[PDB]
């Protein structure tokens, strides 16, 4: 394998961390290959679930808790801290909230959250590498509670960053928020990618094509599929009661990705930087409810 940039994996990984048996598990937690029986039963299906009142309540609670856990991660972003230490703190923060960390053993994923530094687009595996000043780093959190998953991500600055970092992170955030702004019943899911790409393209950046936003509730990933690039052919129309994510991955250079021999880590083919943001949204009559918003602060961590 020829690495696309300077980043390398830092092994060995610590033994996987157990989740105490009192915390409710998703079906895949104990499947040997980490397969989700309830997801695979609905594979290849465009049909979007419409959430009941108790579904909505369950989605509200878990996305609130997921935010709390991301805020925990954010507080630890500094030079010399390893992504593995972030993951350990994340893992304990999920347990304290009586939640299962959804990434853990998801299709055998080894860790409790995804940490994506610089050229890693998404799905970075927490490891022994100390964060370096100048780095940007995305932490993507999902929690599982009483049957429901809640999912969000933010990109952070590691100490002081160069001007290109500031710009890429800002634009990425702007892309997310412009797409959230257009969410309301009757809007086509395929339109969000037109908005995202138009904004990224205007700022000299490209949009990753191989990963998408997703529906989420009792399933971690399900219908709808939500591309972040223009002229995509996404199937579906937004409706009051739909719950899904927008999670645009935006690149300094070109849009193309490939995966490390670990089966998970997705990196730019040119080794330039990528940034990402994610909220889980609920479609309402006025627009959408941002289930994963910060409740006690106006902005994402990179601003404050
Ligand atoms: C954004 C995103 N993230 C993930 C993801 C998975 C694991 C971790 Cl640790 C972090 N993120 N998985 C995703 N999708 C997984 C997905 N699975 C959803 C359920 C389908 C069940 C199924 C049936 C047969 C073969 C594969 C999958 C899928 C599988 C194959 C092609 C596209 C998407 C997505 Cl969209
Ligand atoms: Co993912
Ligand atoms: Co996520
Ligand atoms: Co997601
Ligand atoms: K990154």
Image (spheres, rainbow, N blue to C red):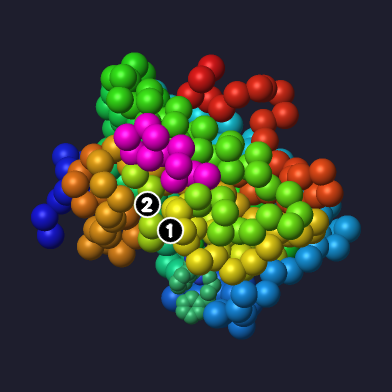
Pointer 2 local density, CA inside 10 Å: few below 14, some 14–19, many at least 20: many
Of the numbered discs in the image, which one, if any, rests on residue 208? 2
**Where is the N terminus found, in terms of image quarters?**
bottom left
Residue drawn at x 50%, y 50% as measured from the top left: 194
> Taking 253 as reference, is 302 left or right?
right
Of the numbered discs in the image, which one, if any, rests on residue 211? 1
Residue drawn at x 86%, y 59% as measured from the top left: 54
Residue 8, image x and y in percent? 20, 45
Residue 116 picture quarter: top left
Residue 34, image x and y in percent? 48, 72
Q: How many marks?
A: 2
Residue drawn at x 76%, y 54% as measured from the top left: 185
Element on which disc 1 rests: loop
In the image, residue 204 lies in the stretch drawn in magenta: yes
Q: Dots 1 and 2: beta carbons under 8 Å?
A: yes
Q: CA distance from mark 1 to mark 2?
A: 7 Å
Residue 148 picture quarter: bottom right
């Amino acid at each position: 394998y020829r690495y696309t940039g300077k980043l390398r994996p830092h092994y060995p990984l610590m033994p996987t961390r157990p989740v105490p048996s009192y915390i409710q598990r998703p079906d895949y937690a104990d499947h040997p290959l980490g397969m989700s029986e309830s997801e695979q039963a609905l594979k290849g299906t465009s049909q979007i679930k419409l959430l009941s009142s108790e579904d909505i309540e369950g989605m509200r609670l878990v996305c609130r808790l997921a935010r709390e856990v991301l805020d925990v991660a954010a507080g630890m972003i500094k030079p010399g801290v390893t992504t593995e230490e972030i993951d350990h703190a994340v893992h304990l923060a999920c347990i304290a909230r009586n939640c299962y960390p959804s990434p853990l053993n998801y299709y055998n994923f080894p860790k409790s959250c995804c940490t994506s530094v610089n050229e890693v687009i998404c799905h970075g595996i927490p490891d022994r590498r100390p964060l370096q000043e100048g780095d940007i780093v995305n932490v993507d959190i999902t929690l599982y509670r009483n049957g429901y998953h809640g999912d969000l991500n933010e990109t952070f600055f590691v100490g002081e960053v160069d001007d290109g970092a500031r710009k890429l992170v800002q634009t990425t955030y702007e892309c997310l928020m412009q797409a959230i702004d257009a969410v309301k019943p009757g809007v086509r899911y395929r339109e969000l990618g037109n908005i995202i790409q138009k904004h990224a393209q205007a700022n000299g950046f490209s949009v990753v094509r191989s990963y998408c936003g997703h529906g989420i509730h009792k399933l971690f990933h399900t219908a709808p599929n939500v591309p972040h690039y223009a002229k995509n052919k996404a199937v579906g129309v937004m409706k009051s009661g739909h719950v899904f994510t927008i999670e645009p991955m935006i690149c300094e250079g070109g849009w193309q990705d490939e995966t490390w021999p670990d089966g998970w880590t997705a990196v730019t083919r040119d080794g330039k930087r990528s940034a990402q943001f994610e909220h889980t949204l609920l479609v309402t009559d006025t627009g959408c409810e941002i289930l994963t918003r910060r409740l006690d602060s106006a902005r994402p961590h990179f601003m404050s």
